[PDB]
Image (tube, rainbow, N blue to C red):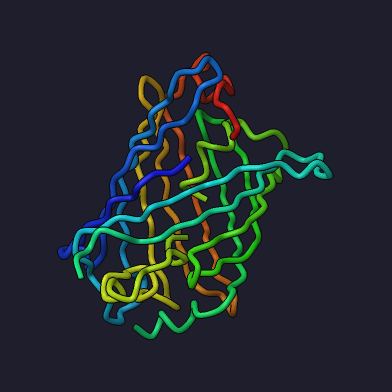
Length: 226
């Protein structure tokens, strides 16, 4: 539904760390916890903004396109930064920016690819994207991939602009790495590069999933979609 992404500076890496729990609803009415550990490091050599502690309030709305027979996810996201008392990359995000997402995954040896396209509006902190599993049936539930599938589109308030690492790393971009531990189940290890290619903000991801249970909530597709 809505979750808070907590961010802190990682000076030794000239980047940031983040941590947060996603609570996925299970079809039986329980919750599947997903503990996220995140690291971001700049790709280029330019100076970046290292933030004070803060968080991203993130709301995700998942839907289906009834005209689409392929395995897919329609996604609307709203992100606004908060939690702080009262760059050139900033200028790249003043308007509506096209987005391209490419993911190649391997979960317990099940290979799959996802392609997403849409647009981001950082002024309002809004993203709209459609994702397609281009290899067939997605071997994991769409909700478990949302966090992996561009926090440069967060709306940072005026009083927090000096804490926006994500835009400050652009256009050269940043590396985003996560360990996602699903409670009583497997782990995603992800590495993404987020950067401008021409006028498009591109998120290129590799995902490895280990230790998942064949009868668990993830490989068993027991998670509610929305």
